[PDB]
């Protein structure tokens, strides 16, 4: 997938969620934003982490996605569509990413297992004793205040 | 900090190791200075740059 | 008798011939050729010949051991000369002058003296205020004390090797690298205490803000004006931040014990000052590893000491107890058959 | 002790610009506590005139007689009211002796010679020697003036004691 | 010999020691009288007609009375708005309530607490202490800037897409707590306060965040003042009556004479830099040798 | 090494395990400990008393609880919600002239005062006071002062007051029979051990 | 005695010894003058403590003795204390332009302005910060501005002292700009103000009745640029004092020149006493500089 | 000489520099100059002058007192420092004299 | 260190005989350069009509001195002295030396036997004992202060008394600083600077003892303030009522006062101090050269 | 930052290095990537770790 340069900060490390967000326009009408750039929208995020990660997305297109999240009449999950996890970048002025749809995350020749990264504020466990396996879920919970 | 790949690639010598306590205890209680304890089969020793 | 009961501590340094065991080729000693350096004087010509040595351990665990084997003399006096607080805090005076003059005439201290400036204390290493006495018949001395309650149960706090702080402040019982649990184990009081299942034994000695705590934490001494040269025997039991900094896994604690947790007392002076990073001698202290002090033979009355001395070998081992009098017995017979053994 | 002479000479040398008169004081345990006297930063006085406002303003009329009118923007006038309020105070000298003493035996332990009519040997735990100024507009002086003693600690808090000019010079002006 | 003024100053000595009181007869400070002062050699005149003492006592009466006439203005405003609404007050502060409860007795206790608080008013209270930040140095530009930032237009996408990033949901409130189970009145009280986001009411906590728990006590009553001089008087059950404190019937220089907030100058041990962490106080003390 | 001097064994748990060996005449100077005998580097009976500890007992830092008060007030009230019962004081100040008629007016309420802390340090016996069942162990900091946490203008402020005499020590730290034996020692000092 | 050995506690990486070996012939201040020392006593980081006062570091740094760094071999660096009058070489770590024929002083590290925080040596909780080897006119200007900031700031509100100190902290020296980080009012600074005040009053008393009026005589006589630029200052002084006119001077009545010679001698004594409080001693006088200003050699001790 | 020797120290600095100091006390009618030999651990000149000013402010007030009490007579100075060298803390011997003495005939540096 | 000073001109052997009499004399050099021409030799690089005295004493602070060692036919071996070691120098100036005297260096204004070329001349600074150096320094400075009023005649008698100088076998004529009823420019700045420093010393201490005695106020400040009162009373005694100093001053005028005081104090260090160069040892007979230790 | 002592002590290939401008001009006006110019004779080449 292609992506403009304004979003690929906190993305040179391999392994991070990637969710395509909707956009009511015609030409840029789909846009691929990372989970960390969604961190300037969650009320779960504290002020320190928010002022940290908003001070890295001070480019043109990041604030455009920030406005596009807060301009429609709909919710977020009627505009967010998950694509999965990246494994490589290409680092142009229009960077090329390789997302992983289904399966593990690895390098070419399988020499390095990439790891999924999630920021500490969004993490949440409901048990002190994890099992042999635990699945992962993405939870959006709306505050209708 | 420590090239642990060169330990896994270069040919070693064979010595009878006699740790004082159990070796996982001496690892977990940090007698030695730099450790690279893990489990499974790391493919880290293959991507040589 | 006033309405409390002070209890003293002291540090007593012996002279030890320790034996050393090591397996075959425990280390490898790498040397090289000697290197000369020429220093020109007007008359002499002094060459400093040098030779550098790298020692590499050839063992996995502790391949070499030692043991404390034989003592021959005691360097200190093992006396009861009380530590002069007026010389380790030469600045704190009473507010009204005449009561201060009367206290100085009551005790032995003559006058307060001003502490040195910051730059002077940068240039010189320390104070070394007190004078060497004329005739030093028994060796050097130290005895420092803590104000305790007279209802401290002596049978479990003065007959076994116990930490005189009030709580068992052994950091090694704490799980390592945990700072909250450490202050939960040594400062809080709404929980049990290790080695004695009460909350504490002295409320004037355990928690933060005791006179022991404000008088023997070194940070509380820096908060006021203290003297640095003198050695405090209490200071290993109340420098809290050093003990929190000693909270590692126990191999590292042993390494710091044999590497950094050895102390300095100069052997030539009549009191016990501290070395100023001296390379002369490092004094091995096993009490700092365990945070426990050892009970020495103390006797209330003359007659109980007399029937201690009349008894044979092992008479010091017991602990006789009269109505209001009591004898604590030594847990090791180092007053019984050390000086007699010579 | 040593501040009283200096302030005497200072008010002598500054007499023609403002005709202040020296007022050498001592304060003790009846006034402020020893915890307050050990951290006492500086003192402040103000020669408020007989009938009206103060010395640091215009004599007749100003722009501070108006109501405050309960506004958010210029809540009390603005910054100019702050400047007028800061200008009207003057800083007196200051010297505190935080050890117990007796005043007459202190001054005899210094070089002075106190000849009091009868031994009013006052005792105290701490003596702070302050020295205010009080104004005479012309060379005469009214007794209806008042003083405002302001004692400042470094936290920002203060205390204020006030007393007239009549009780200050009830006998000593009548002794000349 | 041009002999110095210092030696004749000391050897001239001091005439007599005279003590004096303040006007309220609270402090008693002593005054020395040196003979070698220049006070003698100016030949001052002195007189005090009684009309000047009367005017001086009236001016000092005004200087003492400005605080209590402000408190009386507060009480008059309370009774004015309580007559004005007709007796029906809303709940402006979050507290769970019950329906089956006697409420006329809470009105009686509220009147009792109001009279008790008027009996025990003092210059160390809510409205004075909340007024002291308002009299400060940079208060004018701060309130002007807060007014302009409040009254700013809806931002266009230009300043959101390229301009600088935008930006006090809690307040520093001052409180007078009165209580009639013991007739104990508490004057200088500070309260941290903000809105409950689940509703529209206020939540009052300590600076530690205690969630201040006197509102459930049925006998207390509190007065709240805000830094923008909004007024609150809360009876138990979370109901309260609101107003503005009106000081427009008062002079300006009296308010600056009485409790204008202090500004400090530089002494030893103070940063010539503005606003860093200073070291300790100078602390000339008698416990040490004075060096 | 460490050793105690001048302690007080309880009387109700008193005993003798050396009866045949020692026999002391029953004066009070042998019935209350004030010395300690140790051994020197030579096997010689040295002696320490309270007299020789004057280089420590009389220091002006021992009577200054101001860093103790600062350390006591920085860790403020106990955060335990089970012990929100002992930190209640109302220490007001009122005139005294109207008190002689306000004293029947004080009991016109029917609501009690909460229990003071110094009262709460006296209902423990000599041997449980060191246990965790005591609540007030965070108040006892110094044998010369009383430390407390209770309330002025609805804010818990720390308050350090000096114990002017030795009677203000708690009975768990200073019991009554100990005072009685101390007075007996005083009566022996004045040659008065048989009183008239 | 001339050579001292400082040994490190930590193990040294390749990066550590590589950073050290570029520091040959650099300045190191050592307080203690002991033959063997640990690295905690090295340099200046043992006394670097902000929010305390730049005059404190300027005072204690004045007492510390100096050395040069050479023969670094790992776990030892072998500092060499220079003696008087011999020819040694010095590498300036601080970005100060050096010129030949110039005399050097030692100042505490005032930051360049970007706050680079180039500690140039890595330990876990230790840094090697260095004092700035600075030419004499810059250090003289630093002491002068420090004393001016000291005398001016008494009894002033934060407003006027902020609007003055923000101008006064900025210095310029040869296309550079530095500031004074911790200019606070301290005890040594206070007693230096009192001695400066005593000295200035002694200059006031020990002036004759003709040296006081010489600028008045030239103000009648001549009009140069600096005549006007001094006459405006004295005119504003005399106008703030009196609202009259500054009088023409008179004829010299009592001339008896031995009084004038002794008067100028006492003036010279008090003026040298005042001048020494801003002048520091010369710790290095250069011989020749590198064209890169990276090092030079100097004929003086430490 | 035990009379001229003095210090303000515990003399536990390692390198004890020495300093000749004279003063000019004008409490006497003409002058009462107190000549002194002074050791010190401190080596730098200026901070030593500041410590001496802190120790000898009575002679400074006497100096200003001489200046006000007699305008025609010129006050010469207040005191003159001159270092002589440096020794070690064990080289002293209680008349106190020194076994080794490095010399440094420094300059007459005045102070007020 | 050695310096080789050559001559591009032709050197006559009579001038070699003149120059070998300068076997070891002090010469200054502007920068320590190993190979140098002779145009930087001496003080002829700074001589003019307009600069005069204080410019040369200022430029002598930063110059490095050196000694001639030997003479080759077209280059001179100059030898920079180092501290502690001792050398034999020659008494160039007119004063004769005595043992133990600290020798200072001064530009030769009166000078009047020198190396002569077509445009370049050799001039060597006077090596004078330090008390005479300070003596003629303050003599020239007072003679510069008196320079504006010499239309009167008792001041002409004063400067005539100040003209000569008393020393051992010494009656010198120090040259007049004022030429054609005008002063040379650096002395004009020097006398103006000490005049204005004497003015601001009067006009600022009356504020600053008040500003400083709000701290601990010892008797030093009290007698200082009384002395200031004596100065004020003896100043304005023939004047109207008082100068009447105010308390609320503008900040920036005070900054411009104090910075000017210090920056004009800065340009008087060359006159108030003396570079000591040599401490002399045992002198030759008839006092024309001497072995001396270089205390630099 | 490379080890310039390794460049110094290793034997080099002699090349007729003839670029266009002056050497100091092409250095100080930043033609190359990482420059390192010692003017004297640096002894850092003689310390081997």
Image (tube, coloured by chain):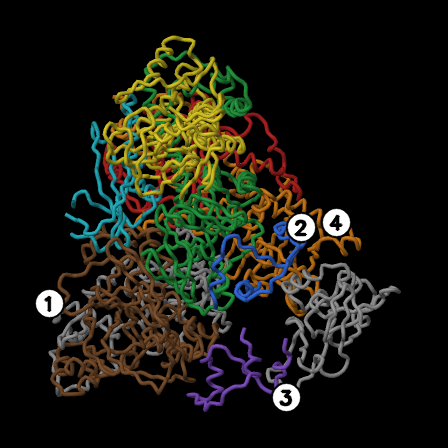
Chain colours: B purple, C brown, D red, E orange, G green, H cyan, I yellow, J blue
Q: Give the residue at mark 3.
A: A132
Residue C293 at x, y percent in the picture: 30, 76
Whether residue H112 is visible, yes or no, is yes
Q: Give the residue at mark 4.
A: E152
| Residue furthest to the front | I13
**Given contact means CB atoms under 8 Å apart, are the residues at marks 4 and 3 in contact?**
no
Disc number at residue J21? 2
Disc 4 to disc 3, C-alpha distance = 56 Å
Q: Residues within 10 Å of mark 2 (few under 14, many from 20)?
A: few
The reply to whether label 2 and label 1 mark residues of one chain is no
Whether residue I62 is visible, yes or no, is no
**Given contact means CB atoms under 8 Å apart, are the residues at marks 1 and 4 in contact?**
no
Give the secondary structure at mark 4. Answer: loop
**Given contact means CB atoms under 8 Å apart, are the residues at marks 3 and 1 in contact?**
no
Disc 3 to disc 2, C-alpha distance = 70 Å
Q: Is residue C134 above or below residue G213?
A: below
The chain identifier of the residue carrying mark 4 reads E
Q: Residues within 10 Å of mark 3 (few under 14, many from 20)?
A: few
The reply to whether label 3 and label 1 mark residues of one chain is no
| Residue G162 quadrant | top right
Indicate left or right for G78 with F155 as reference: left
Which one is in front in this view, the residue at disc 3 or the one at disc 2?
Answer: 2
Which one is in front in this view, the residue at disc 4 or the one at disc 2?
Answer: 2
Which one is in front in this view, the residue at disc 3 or the one at disc 1?
Answer: 3
Q: Give the residue at mark 1.
A: F191
- For the residue pair G179 and I238, the one nearer the viewer reads as G179
**Given contact means CB atoms under 8 Å apart, are the residues at marks 2 and 1 in contact?**
no
Indicate left or right for J9 with D23 as reference: right
């Amino acid at each position: 997938f292609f992506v403009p340069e304004g979003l690929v900060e906190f993305e040179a490390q391999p392994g991070a969620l990637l969710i395509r967000m909707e956009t009511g326009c015609d030409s840029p009408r789909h846009l691929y934003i990372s989970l960390y750039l969604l961190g300037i929208r969650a009320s779960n995020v504290s002020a320190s982490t928010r002022c940290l990660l908003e001070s890295v997305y001070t480019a043109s297109a990041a604030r455009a996605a920030l406005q596009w999240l807060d301009l429609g009449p709909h919710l977020l999950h009627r505009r967010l569509e998950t694509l999965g996890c990246v494994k490589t970048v290409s680092l142009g002025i229009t960077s090329l990413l390789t997302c992983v749809m289904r399966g593990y995350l690895y390098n070419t020749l399988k020499t390095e297992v990439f790891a999924l990264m999630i920021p500490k504020d969004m993490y949440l466990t409901w048990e002190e004793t994890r099992g042999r396996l635990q699945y992962v879920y993405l939870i959006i919970v709306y505050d209708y205040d | 900090m420590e090239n642990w790949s060169a330990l896994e690639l270069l040919p070693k010598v064979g010595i009878p190791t006699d740790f004082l306590t159990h070796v996982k205890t001496s690892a977990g209680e940090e007698m030695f200075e730099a450790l690279r304890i893990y489990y499974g089969d790391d493919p880290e020793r293959y991507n040589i740059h | 008798h006033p309405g409390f009961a002070l209890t003293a501590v002291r540090t007593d340094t012996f002279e030890v011939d320790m034996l050393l065991y090591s397996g075959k080729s425990c280390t490898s000693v790498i040397i090289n050729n000697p290197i000369v350096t020429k220093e020109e004087r007007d008359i002499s010509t002094t060459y400093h010949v040098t030779q550098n040595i790298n020692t590499v351990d050839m063992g996995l665990g502790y391949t070499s051991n030692t043991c404390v084997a034989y003592v021959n003399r005691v360097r200190t006096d093992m006396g009861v000369r009380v530590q002069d607080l007026f010389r380790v805090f030469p600045m704190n005076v009473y507010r009204h002058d005449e009561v201060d003059r009367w206290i100085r005439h009551a005790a032995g201290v003559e006058r307060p003296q001003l502490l040195d400036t910051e730059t002077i204390s940068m240039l010189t290493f320390g104070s070394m205020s007190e004078r060497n006495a004329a005739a030093t018949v028994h060796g050097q001395k130290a005895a420092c004390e803590l104000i305790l309650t007279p209802v401290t149960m002596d049978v479990n706090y003065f007959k076994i090797p116990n930490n005189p702080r009030g709580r068992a402040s052994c950091m090694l019982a704490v799980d390592p690298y945990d700072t909250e649990a450490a202050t939960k184990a040594i400062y809080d009081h709404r929980e049990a205490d290790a080695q004695t299942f009460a909350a504490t034994h002295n409320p004037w000695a355990s928690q933060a803000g005791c006179l022991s705590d404000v008088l023997y934490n070194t940070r509380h001494r820096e908060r006021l004006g203290y003297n640095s040269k003198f050695y405090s025997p209490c200071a290993q039991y109340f420098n809290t931040e050093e003990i929190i900094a000693a909270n590692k896994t126990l191999f590292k604690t042993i390494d710091e014990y044999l590497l950094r947790a050895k102390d300095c007392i100069r052997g030539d002076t009549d009191t016990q000052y501290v070395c100023v990073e001296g390379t002369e001698q490092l004094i091995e202290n096993p009490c700092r590893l365990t945070q426990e002090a050892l009970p020495i033979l103390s006797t209330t009355t003359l007659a109980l000491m007399e029937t201690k001395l009349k008894g044979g070998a092992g008479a010091f081992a017991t602990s006789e107890t009269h109505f209001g009098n009591y004898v604590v017995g030594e847990i090791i017979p180092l007053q019984q058959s050390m000086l007699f053994n010579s | 002790m040593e501040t009283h002479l200096y302030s005497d000479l200072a008010f002598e040398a500054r007499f023609a610009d403002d005709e202040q008169l020296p007022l050498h004081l001592v304060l003790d345990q009846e006034v402020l506590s020893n915890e307050e006297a050990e951290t006492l930063r500086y003192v402040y006085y103000r020669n408020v005139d007989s009938a009206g406002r103060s010395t640091g303003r215009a004599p007749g009329g100003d722009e501070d007689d108006a109501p405050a009118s309960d506004d958010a923007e210029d809540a009390v006038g603005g910054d100019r009211a702050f400047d007028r309020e800061r200008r009207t105070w003057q800083r007196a000298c200051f010297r505190v002796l935080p050890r117990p003493l007796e005043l007459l035996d202190y001054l005899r332990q210094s070089g002075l010679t106190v000849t009091l009519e009868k031994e009013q040997r006052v005792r105290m735990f701490y003596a702070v020697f302050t020295t205010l100024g009080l104004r005479c507009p012309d060379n005469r002086l009214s007794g209806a003036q008042t003083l405002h003693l302001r004692l400042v600690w470094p936290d920002g808090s203060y205390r204020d004691w006030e007393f007239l000019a009549r009780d200050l010079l009830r006998e000593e002006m009548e002794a000349n | 010999d041009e002999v110095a003024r210092t030696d004749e100053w000391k050897g001239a000595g001091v005439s007599r020691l005279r003590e004096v009181w303040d006007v309220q007869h609270r402090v008693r400070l002593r005054v020395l009288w040196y003979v070698n002062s220049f006070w003698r050699s100016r030949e001052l005149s002195y007189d005090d007609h009684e009309v000047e003492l009367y005017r001086a006592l009236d001016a000092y009466r005004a200087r003492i009375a400005v605080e209590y006439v402000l408190i009386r203005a507060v009480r008059d405003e309370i009774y004015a708005v309580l007559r004005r609404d007709g007796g029906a007050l809303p709940q402006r502060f979050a507290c769970h309530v019950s329906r089956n409860m006697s409420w006329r007795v809470v009105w009686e206790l509220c009147r009792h607490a109001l009279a008790l608080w008027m009996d025990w008013a003092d210059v160390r209270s809510c409205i004075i202490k909340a007024l002291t930040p308002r009299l400060s140095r940079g208060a004018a530009a701060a309130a002007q800037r807060a007014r302009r930032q409040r009254e700013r237009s809806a931002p266009k996408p230009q300043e959101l897409l390229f301009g600088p990033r935008n930006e006090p949901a809690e307040q520093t409130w001052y409180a007078d707590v009165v209580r009639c189970v013991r007739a104990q009145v508490d004057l200088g009280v500070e309260v941290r306060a903000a809105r409950c986001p689940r509703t529209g009411l206020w939540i009052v906590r300590d600076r530690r965040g205690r969630l201040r728990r006197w509102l459930s006590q049925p006998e207390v009553c509190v007065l709240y003042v805000t830094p923008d001089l909004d007024f609150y008087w809360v009876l138990p059950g979370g109901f309260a009556v609101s107003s503005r404190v009106t000081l427009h019937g008062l002079a300006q220089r009296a308010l600056r004479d009485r409790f204008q907030n202090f500004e400090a100058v530089l002494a030893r041990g103070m940063h010539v830099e503005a606003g860093r962490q200073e070291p300790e106080t100078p602390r000339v003390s008698g416990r040490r040798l004075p060096f | 090494f460490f050793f105690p001097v001048g302690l007080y064994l309880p009387e109700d748990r008193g005993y003798t395990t050396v009866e045949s060996k020692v026999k002391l005449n029953d004066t009070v100077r042998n019935a209350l400990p004030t010395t300690a005998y140790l051994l020197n580097r030579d096997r010689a009976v040295q002696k320490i008393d309270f007299v020789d500890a004057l280089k420590t007992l009389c220091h002006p830092v021992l009577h200054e609880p101001a860093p103790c008060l600062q350390t006591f007030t920085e860790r403020g009230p106990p955060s335990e919600p089970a012990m929100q019962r002992l930190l209640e004081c109302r220490f007001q100040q009122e005139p005294m002239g109207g008190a002689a008629r306000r004293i029947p007016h004080f009991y016109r309420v029917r609501r009690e005062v909460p229990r003071t802390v110094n009262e709460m340090k006296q209902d423990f016996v000599v041997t449980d006071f060191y246990k965790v069942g005591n609540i007030t162990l965070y108040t006892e900091l110094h044998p010369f002062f009383d430390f407390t946490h209770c309330q002025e203008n609805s804010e818990t402020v720390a308050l350090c007051t000096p114990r002017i005499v030795i009677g203000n020590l708690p009975d768990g730290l200073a019991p009554g029979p100990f005072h009685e034996l101390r007075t007996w020692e005083i009566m022996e000092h004045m040659r008065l051990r048989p009183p008239p | 005695e001339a050579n001292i050995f400082c040994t490190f506690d930590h193990k040294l990486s390749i990066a550590d010894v590589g950073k050290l070996t570029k520091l040959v012939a650099a300045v190191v201040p050592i307080p203690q003058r002991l033959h063997l020392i640990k690295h905690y006593q090295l340099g200046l980081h043992q006394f670097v403590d902000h929010t305390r006062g730049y005059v404190r570091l300027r005072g204690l740094l004045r007492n510390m003795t100096l050395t040069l760094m050479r023969r670094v071999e790992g776990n030892q660096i072998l500092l060499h204390v220079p003696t008087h009058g011999l020819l040694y070489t010095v590498l300036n770590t601080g970005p100060v332009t050096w010129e030949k024929g110039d005399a050097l002083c030692v100042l505490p590290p005032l930051f360049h302005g970007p706050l680079a925080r180039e500690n140039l040596l890595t330990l876990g909780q230790w840094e090697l910060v260095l004092p700035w080897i600075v030419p004499m006119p810059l250090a003289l200007e630093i002491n002068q501005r420090l004393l001016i900031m000291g005398l001016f700031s008494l009894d002033r509100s934060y407003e006027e002292v902020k609007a003055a100190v923000q101008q006064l902290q900025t210095i310029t020296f040869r296309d550079a700009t530095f500031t004074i980080p911790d200019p606070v009012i301290d005890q040594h600074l206070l007693i230096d103000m009192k001695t400066a005040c005593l000295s200035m009053s002694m200059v006031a008393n020990l002036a004759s009745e003709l040296t006081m009026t010489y600028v008045r005589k030239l103000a009648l006589e001549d009009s140069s640029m600096l005549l006007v630029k001094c006459q405006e200052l004295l005119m504003r002084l005399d106008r703030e004092r009196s609202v009259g006119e500054p009088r023409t001077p008179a004829r010299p009545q009592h001339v008896s020149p031995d009084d004038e010679i002794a008067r100028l001698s006492a003036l010279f004594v008090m003026l040298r006493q005042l001048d020494d409080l801003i002048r520091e001693q010369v710790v290095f006088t250069v011989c020749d500089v590198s064209p890169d200003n990276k090092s030079a050699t100097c004929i003086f001790k430490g | 000489p035990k009379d001229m020797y003095l210090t303000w120290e515990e003399t536990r600095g390692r390198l004890q520099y020495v300093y000749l100091i004279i003063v000019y006390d004008y409490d006497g009618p003409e002058t009462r100059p107190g000549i002194y030999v002074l050791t010190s651990s401190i080596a730098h000149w200026q901070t030593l002058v500041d410590v001496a000013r802190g120790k000898f402010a009575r002679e400074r007030c006497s100096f200003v007192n001489r200046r006000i009490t007699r305008p025609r007579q010129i006050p010469l100075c207040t005191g003159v420092i001159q270092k002589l060298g440096w020794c070690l803390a064990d080289d002293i011997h209680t008349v106190v004299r020194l076994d080794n003495f490095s010399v440094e005939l420094g300059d007459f540096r005045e102070f007020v």
